[PDB]
Image (cartoon, rainbow over all chains, first blue to last red; front, side, top):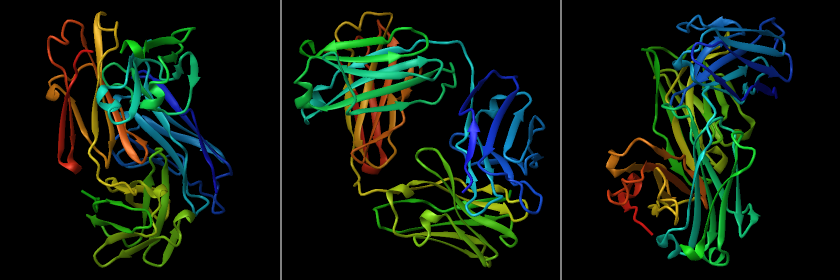
Length: 220
Length: 218
């Protein structure tokens, strides 16, 4: 069972820049026969994986010379001399020296850099239609922000709430390179009618203080 | 071209069974390591099984005794018989051709989805998300749509039948009580709504349902 560790998990770059992805194995990948079966694959959204480099440094047929691989033993590196738009996606390293099973690293997402952007936060109360069914979802959108790291906190009558929260994140926007997130706090109609103040708090590098959006139920 | 034509996937209840297959096109299986891989919901790539010239067989431990890989070298068709299916087996499966000598996989079939669940076909409930009291007088206003409790994936969501495309963010579905929930927001100039109508259109093929929800004030 060879564990493969890739660093970093996310690599923001500007088109034209050089990029380097690292991969480390829990054991040396040098086989008894002298070969090192370490490979690099790329998988784009909605597509199947594509082989880029095999046995550490052999570029597969058809792959651009901008891709090169190096390393030995337990540490390897995939380099892209000049990043192009078509190179954006997830890069996976994989070992087939100790098999079975053949194993893969968790992947590294090559993404685009852009100027920082604070999220535009909007909060929404449960709809009258949902309440009629006995449910009450409070929704919060945290839109068009950068970088992608962000934290969301829900508060009911001023106290932190953790149960019932479900989050969803979009992939980087192809037009403006920002990220967006949707957070939904689902309660029963009973619980919703039991409290009045509902708050969505966002913590993002663009602010020393959490960004806050809130509303009171008895007002609507 | 050289390729692998993948079979259609399927929906299966836990404990059930299903068979996948891939046909070679432009090449022959002999000499290659034919294998099955899968991309889990968490987005992790996993090797599942391999077979070489019909006499060398390997399996990921978690599928031994449940999955069976076989090959018809005459017709050049790879199979994956999945039995005693579990929720954890839900994923996008790929068949692939690998070099026996260098141990890499260069030819991959298109992904085939296998969903293991006890859920029954369910139409989604589409809820309008109207701005709270006080957030309707800025330069722009954001409206939303909550699509809750449907199965199976996917649904098609548009705003104003598709004419409203900019400033829209539709989020990936998440599981909630074994059913899917998705949301979408649209941001427009403050003077646009509600003088001009904004409608969330949700289509769910599986249930032949089309729901249009107008977003209205208060």
